[PDB]
Length: 233
Length: 235
Ligand SMILES: Nc1ncnc2c1ncn2[C@@H]1O[C@H](COP(=O)(O)OP(=O)(O)O)[C@@H](O)[C@H]1O
Ligand SMILES: Nc1ncnc2c1ncn2[C@@H]1O[C@H](COP(=O)(O)OP(=O)(O)O)[C@@H](O)[C@H]1O
Ligand SMILES: [Cl-]
Ligand SMILES: [Mg+2]
Ligand SMILES: [Mg+2]
Image (cartoon, rainbow over all chains, first blue to last red; front, side, top):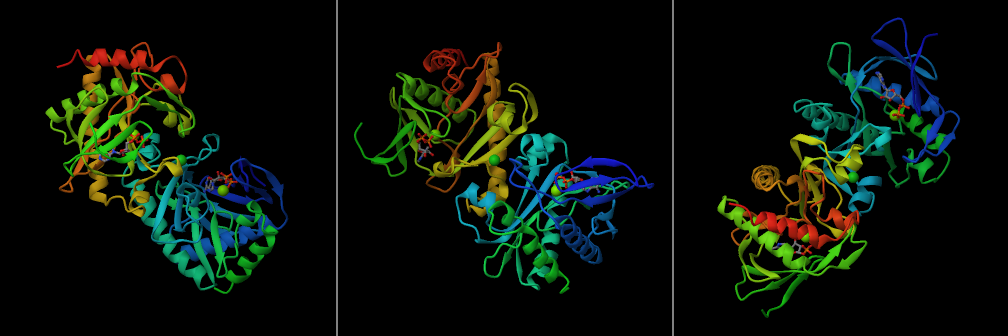
């Protein structure tokens, strides 16, 4: 029992007795594109929290610095408390969704090398897509910081892409958040579940949140499958 | 004036010459809004525009900027070097206005220091979407060293334009360049620099450009003329 700091779409965050520490609670809320249509859909909290806890651990083993300490419940994990960088970092392996729209090209077209993209994590501004100069203007980060957020998201793509391959899923794109820890460094934060990445079945089947949005089945089913496959590592 | 069409634009019909390397540009009386959505014929516009562009482009040539400009042919026409256009629209911002205002949710009118440059892919089917460096490399438009060149040039270009407009009392909020390749493969400033293509605030905050058309604040040629007049007071 401790205090609720922030209340999200997918996560409520609580405090502890350790200033630098935070317990994350994954909710059953699901919400669609920016025009937040809201459905609450059972089991989702637990799968997300499992999957995220797993990958994050795997990353930590692979020496990626992150906010993960331990999965504490079905519903909760304990995380290092960081100061969030309002900058969603998207790395794309394949064309899909908003890249596809922006460039009027289909989804499924491979890229090589992969493209990263910043978005201003500002719900009020509808999390707009931005360029490096916009980030500097916003004073989120200068140079050296921008080049770090890239250089490590790529390293993160390289680990993750391999891992999902091995379980027969192609990492189409994902989305990080990073923040500063009590010691000032930058650190992979938030969560890595099917909610913030795209996953393609070797037959084009969507093993991700595009099931809720496009509406091609029930969510917990594909998530369940991904969770099942991950323990193959 | 009699040769064949190379392509029709919303503002400019560009014709051929006997000189493979040279283009004669024809400025039209047509004005088009947002995503080509609404358009009107406004008399004098092409002429008014044609002088402004020829004048600025001349001044650039004398201040050492490579451009596609050779001479003004007449009211409606000028002669230009043929370029393989770079389908990037390059926007430099000095003050906030319009789209930057939209995306970042703040007022038209705030000084930026430094000025922000922004690429859009010149592709009307896509409504010239806003793109970032890595999209340009994707799109196969330019390599790094070149994107860096487009940047550094649009900057020293602002640092001339801003002054000249200052001296006649005009606030260069933002503009929008286009560059292309000349006969010897050198990047070169081209297209046009009219008030269709930039923002020029009055000291009273009055709109000395196409925002008069967009926001329908009144008629375009009044203002365009006032700028032509003012520009003629320079050197
Ligand atoms: N280590 C951390 N310290 C502080 N805040 C965090 C940390 N990790 C994630 N967060 C934030 O917790 C919030 C969780 O709510 P969530 O529903 O994920 O947000 P969103 O609705 O933006 O997706 C997010 O705004 C995220 O930035
Ligand atoms: N020197 C040049 N050589 C060849 N094409 C040019 C040159 N300068 C401009 N252009 C192109 O000619 C067209 C001019 O039509 P315009 O109405 O200005 O285009 P838009 O409707 O895209 O604004 C544009 O596609 C522009 O890029
Ligand atoms: Cl955009
Ligand atoms: Mg989130
Ligand atoms: Mg044009």
